[PDB]
Image (cartoon, rainbow over the protein chains, first blue to last red):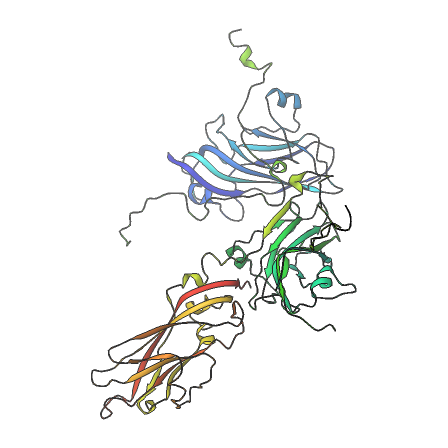
Amino acid sequence: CLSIPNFPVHITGKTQQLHVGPKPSIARFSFNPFDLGTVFNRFQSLCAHLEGYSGDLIVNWLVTCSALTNARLYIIPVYDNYSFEKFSEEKLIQCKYEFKQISLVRKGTVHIPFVNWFGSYSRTRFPKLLFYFPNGVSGPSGEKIHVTVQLDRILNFSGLGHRLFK
Amino acid sequence: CLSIPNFPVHITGKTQQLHVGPKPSIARFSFNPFDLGTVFNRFQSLCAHLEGYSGDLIVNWLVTCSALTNARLYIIPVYDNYSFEKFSEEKLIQCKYEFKQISLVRKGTVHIPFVNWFGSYSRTRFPKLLFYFPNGVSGPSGEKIHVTVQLDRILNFSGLGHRLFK
Amino acid sequence: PDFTKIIWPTVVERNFSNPQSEITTTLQELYGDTFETVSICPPQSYGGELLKGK
Amino acid sequence: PDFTKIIWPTVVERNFSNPQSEITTTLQELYGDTFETVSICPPQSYGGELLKGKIFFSSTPEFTREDLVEGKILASFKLDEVLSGLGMGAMLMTQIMSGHATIRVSAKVMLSKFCSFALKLVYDELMQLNSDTTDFGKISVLPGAIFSTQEEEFSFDFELFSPGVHLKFDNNKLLGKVHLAALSAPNLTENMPESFSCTFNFSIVDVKTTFYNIG
């Protein structure tokens, strides 16, 4: 298997809107570089022939709101490709998750350690990062906050396999 | 020549409007106490017979805006009576000019050292202070910021000449 | 410097170097960057690690 | 206290004493008073202070044999053009709008070992000699020196004079006029070149910038 200590990919995900309101909101960002779009990203140009890879992800996350907008933010990893519609805040506080007020901390970097039951990420196995606003978002009269993430790099990269070039 | 170490004049210039917008803006304040208006200022009451004077100027400057208004401010001296319509920000950063964000610093005192090629200020030779907003002013929906300066005093004053009382 | 320059094949290209980021229009205490690591923590008052041995 | 109180005539009246100012409705870190001093700073990576001691202009004009009569002006240089040319030395100098400049000028003519004539290098400071002057009454008295053009290369310094304290450079077509004047016919005139080549190198001896151009 090829090993890459640092592998920059600079892939930015789609920016996701959130209208202001009291309803609990979730923004899901899957981190699947094997996912193809209009252009092939730096990951696919060099390691798309692989069947699966392994390594820690670094993600730059950003929440753009007004200066008079309040919200609590829970950044939650989701491994092994599970689907969560609702979160139990009791469970999050029991796991010592700390929420951040987007009126004070609305920029950050998330290190995602490698966690997969199968042993590697793939086209079908990838981590998810869920931005969970439990109280919704309280903003000025029709605001939409935007949550945008960028997969910055992959640390301690390892990859195996050899797919067919379709 | 008569010499005055400290000479208070308390002359306030005209307050100048600036509409909010992205266009680069300049507010010019000439400091010409020989300029007459409706009333004779403290400078003219005692030293209007002079042909020209010399000394460092002290100017209190003030920018009145809202609390949700952003702008970068370059306070630029202009000596020898030159006219600048546009400024080269490359040239300003090369001369180590520092801009101030009016959402953080919107009051100040500017010391203007004596700089004139002719050797003195006069009716036609005077310094100018230019408040240059390179990115315009970003304010709440029709705001106008006001820039107002006051010539506080003249330090190390010296004056010569004897004009005719017209 | 000629063609006999030895080339070390690296995957890190210098088309994007140190991305500096500086706060401009407000105070830092009003705008903070957090660096976290999203690891899995079993809960405090329950979780199978209490049944270990039982 | 009576009328014999001695009066010291001061211009500072007590109708406006210490103007205190206090922040009320917000935090200080959100409302700051800056006290600055707007002085002139020459730029960091350019500005005439880098040319101090170095050449900034160079021409190589020519003059014919028939122009080597006594008094004839051979080459001329307006200082307002030498300081506003197209070279890199000049473009660094046109950014200085006002200040001081002491300028060195050097002349050098390439000759055989046969011909040798004397030349005066004059600094006409009020620009009173057009290039079509064969006077020698004006040449003999202008500030400058004579030199032999075969074994020698002659240079001298001159300070640009301002009526005021500094010298406004912007739009100043009255900075002086340097000339190379012929004092005598050549040594030998038969079977000789019909034209010569003189090199002029203007250098900066000293520059001070009292105001710098900004766009």
